[PDB]
Structure formats: structure tokens, C-alpha cells
Image 1 (cartoon, rainbow, N blue to C red):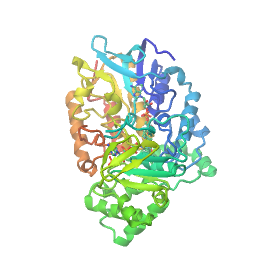
Image 2 (image 1 turned 120 degrees about the vertical axis):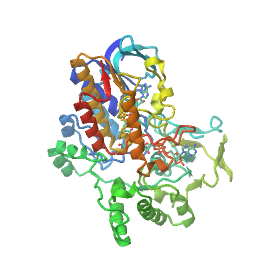
Image 3 (image 1 turned 180 degrees about the horizontal axis):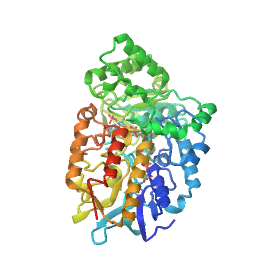
Length: 531
Ligand SMILES: Cc1cc2nc3c(=O)[nH]c(=O)nc-3n(C[C@H](O)[C@H](O)[C@H](O)COP(=O)(O)OP(=O)(O)OC[C@H]3O[C@@H](n4cnc5c(N)ncnc54)[C@H](O)[C@@H]3O)c2cc1C
Ligand SMILES: NC(=O)c1ccc[n+]([C@@H]2O[C@H](COP(=O)([O-])OP(=O)(O)OC[C@H]3O[C@@H](n4cnc5c(N)ncnc54)[C@H](OP(=O)(O)O)[C@@H]3O)[C@@H](O)[C@H]2O)c1
């Protein structure tokens, strides 16, 4: 629109988090406005328009629950929503509640500084706006700053793309020699799409990722009508799980079962499709021998999928425990490699030397290409904030405080930066659960908190230094009882050169985490000092 001078609560970003903050603060009777870089609402589902983009949580799980009207009216069509359909859903929710009048688009926040004189935040943008707001809510997302791989990039003659900043006009790869770098789920979702148009598809793999089949399906309209009858009930069940979905929590240890029961329980998971296998046994994430048992089964499934055993073996992920990078759902990605026009280039054995203007040189050879797609992921969890000059008490940069890894109390707040809040970021369950559930819980908790400051005539909320320190020690310690910290992944910050290695997330589970938050709020926000 045109942003106001002054406001109770300013919110950065218009994706699932932003929009919800906005609605609920209006419903709390507070003044609120949102600033967003993009052209319209959407967040990851506005930016990641690459062909094949699709969620790995079931449509019925990956949605809002705050609005009974919305559960009733909206019709999902598939087990997993593709990106254009999740975007229609966000647009449907935005029209419903007229959220757009609360949002300025095309505008990036560049700086923010806390003024101890007034207990208020002063916020700057790239258009020149300067806004003043008692509270700052960073809803700038976890996987919102695209990351380019590490020499010869401006030299490329052909066309160049990132999956996480995809053009709005569809792209035509017909005829072309095309390369994709990256086999994350971006890489793995967009390749089979490209392999349909192009004359030649080169997939540049570094470390192979474990992917299991999605087995997408139509969503039976009967089933949806039935669920609608019990919908709030259904979400409440998800809200009472470690992961925020209906995944079954395998009670047994993967070491305890026989070999034949392992093959059967797991085979049954492979036929069903989806990520639920992750919780097939309790210790897949807590014990290296358990994990290797599941890992090997899956590796053989990957071997069975391609005819040419030389290529197959290049696709088998090695050297890290199963599940310790995000688990990826594939749809016809492994079958793709049986096509004549698809070539797997291993950069574990022959690293990428440089990009030339014609293509990509490994040690081994040069590869000539007309178009190049980077599926190389994001500066995850801390990227978005690090692009912003944020300054607290004593004029400390957040960049300086968090330089050795994020330091938070509950992930919600950082000491020395009062009245500042982070939605679904480091210090909290974040992307280790269904993010609609993590996100809704944080928005309700932060915004309850704001409501509670106003009713009680307070104006300053800061996390206590020693309570933040204890939360950090707690997060690291529970991380270190699992296999997560063992492995380089975006969870750790490992795909950004020179980024500190630190498992950035709460691994306890959504459910414990919520409990802790409710106790904290119940006690009057213990661990915070309010004045
Ligand atoms: C391709 C993809 C698929 C995903 N699939 C799933 C899934 O399967 N399961 C699941 O649980 N989660 C999934 N996610 C994770 C995703 O982060 C969450 O599900 C959720 O959508 C994040 O919403 P958000 O509002 O918190 O952040 P975002 O959607 O990232 O919204 C942040 C917004 O803030 C904007 N912004 C950033 N900096 C500024 C600034 N300085 N000024 C103004 N605006 C700014 C960004 O442009 C962005 O639009 C996936 C993520 C990606 C990238
Ligand atoms: N189905 C879905 O819902 C979906 C879709 C897209 C994204 N997401 C979310 O967003 C996260 C990001 O997925 P993503 O595929 O975009 O990114 P990613 O998981 O961070 O994977 C990035 C990929 O590019 C490679 N890469 C990065 N830098 C490189 C370099 N300098 N040289 C060579 N190769 C390099 C990595 O190889 P290495 O492993 O060896 O680093 C990896 O293949 C996902 O885990 C998930 O949370 C979800």
C-alpha cells in the first residue's frame, strides 16, 4: 500500500507466518502492518514456482486451523498439494480476511534498531520508509534466502535459474541441453519435469540424498467431507505429536526385530509412500546401528530402481545416517535415470572446477549446456535476518551476537534485544515438524504475549541472559543424544561457506516444546523481564 509512520506491531514477511500474525493481532484489537519484498502474498509458495514444486506433508495436514470457516470451505484435491494449489489457498485466505490492506509489497527491510529511550523499534526499508513500532515480529521464514554454489558463473552464455527465485512466465526447455546442480528436494522435484522437454539432461550430484517415493494420489471427495465433520478434532491430535502430523510412532527398536520383520515392516512403508518411515522405529535417530539397518534397506531399493548397476551405485547415499539431512519424497526421479537423455554426473569423484560460458567443467570433462538450473538451497534459518542490520541494547548487532551460532530463549527471543520475536526459527521445533503447526503455535504465543503486555500496561519484554544461556545448553545437549549433529546439512549451516557448524533446532518434538511454552506463559512469562 504505503506503510504507516507508527504502529503497535510491525511484521516482516507475508507467508504463512506473516498473514497469521496480521489476522490475529487485528482480532486482538492491535494495530499492525506487514512489510514484504515480494509482489504478492505467499512466501515460499510465491517464490518457488519451479515446475514440479509440491509439499511433502499431506494436504490435510499442511493448512491453517485457526478459522473454522476455512477448514469447511476449502477443497484439497491431492494427497500432497502442488505449489500452484497451495498458492491459490493462501490467496483464498487473504481475500477472505482482507489481509492485503495490512501489507506493503515490493519493499525490503534493510535495517532496524531498538531505542531504549522509548522502548520501541525503528525500522528502515529500501524505498526509504521509516516506521516506529512497540514490537517487531520477524516472519521472514526459514528457507527464504536463496543460496548459489561455490567460480565461473557470470561467464555463462545461456540462461541461468534458481529454483527459489523462479520467473513467473513458464520456461521452455524444449530442444535444450540443460544442467541442474543440486539433488535436494528442489533438485529432485524439478529434474523429472525438465527431462520431459530437453534433448539432454545433466544432473550434477554432489552428496546423494535419501529420497523415498511419494505415491501421490487423488484425494477422494468422500474422505474430505468425512474429515470435515471431525476436523478440529483431527488437528488437535496432530498438535499432540512430536512431528505435528498423524505419523505412526514406531514403539520398537530397529535392533530388536529379526531381519524378516525388518524387511516386511519397511516394505510396507515403501508401498504406502511418504516420510512416515522416519518413525518406523524409535531409535532410527538415536543409535547408529539401528539407523544403518534402515539405511541399508533403502539403499537396496535405490539399487533395484535403475538397470545399469554402475549408475545405480552413484545414487546410493553413503557416509551419513539416514534421516539426518531432510528426508525427500521423489516422484519418478529414480526411474528418470533409465532414460537415454538423462545423465548423472558425480561431483564427488570429479569436482566442479569452474562454470565456462558454454557449460560446466569438472576435472574429467566440460559439459556443454544451453540453460543452467541451480537447485542449491538456502542460507537456512539465519539467512533472512543476516541480510538485515538489526541492533539491540548497547547498539549490538544481532549478526555479532549470533556469530558463533544463534542464541535464543525458546527460539522466540534473544537477550539484549527486547520486544523482538522470531517465528518458527532456530531454538525451536521449526522445520523438524509440520510447519503449519509450529508456525500457528508461535504466532498464537507471541501475539497472546503482546495482548498481555497491553492489558497489563507494560512496554518492554526481554529474555533474561542466563535463561537464554540455559536454553542454548539445553538445545545442544538434547541434539547431541541424536545423530543429527554428526552430519553436514542446512540444519547445521553446512551449505554456507564459513558458516559456524551448530545444529540450530529444538529436537525434542513439537508437543514437549508447546508444553514448555505454556508453562512459561502460565507463570507470567518466566525467563522474561517485563517493565
Ligand atoms: C520449496 C519449499 C517447500 C517446503 N515444503 C514444506 C513442507 O513440505 N513441510 C513443511 O513443514 N514446511 C515446508 N517448507 C518450509 C517452509 O519454510 C514452511 O512450511 C513455511 O511455508 C514458511 O513460512 P513462513 O511464513 O514462516 O516463511 P516464508 O514463506 O519463507 O515467508 C517469509 C517472507 O518474508 C519475506 N522477507 C524476507 N526478508 C524480508 C525483508 N527483509 N523484508 C521484507 N520481506 C522479507 C520473504 O520474501 C518471504 O516472502 C518448504 C520450504 C520450501 C522453500
Ligand atoms: N518437497 C518439498 O516440500 C520441498 C521442496 C524444495 C525444498 N524444500 C525444503 O527446503 C530445503 C532445501 O531443499 P533444496 O533442494 O532447495 O536445498 P538443499 O536441501 O539445501 O540441497 C542443496 C543441494 O545442492 C547441492 N549444493 C549446494 N551447494 C553446492 C556447491 N557449492 N557445489 C555443488 N553442489 C552444491 C547440495 O549438494 P550437497 O548435499 O553435497 O551439499 C544439495 O544437492 C529442503 O530440505 C526442504 O526443507 C522442500
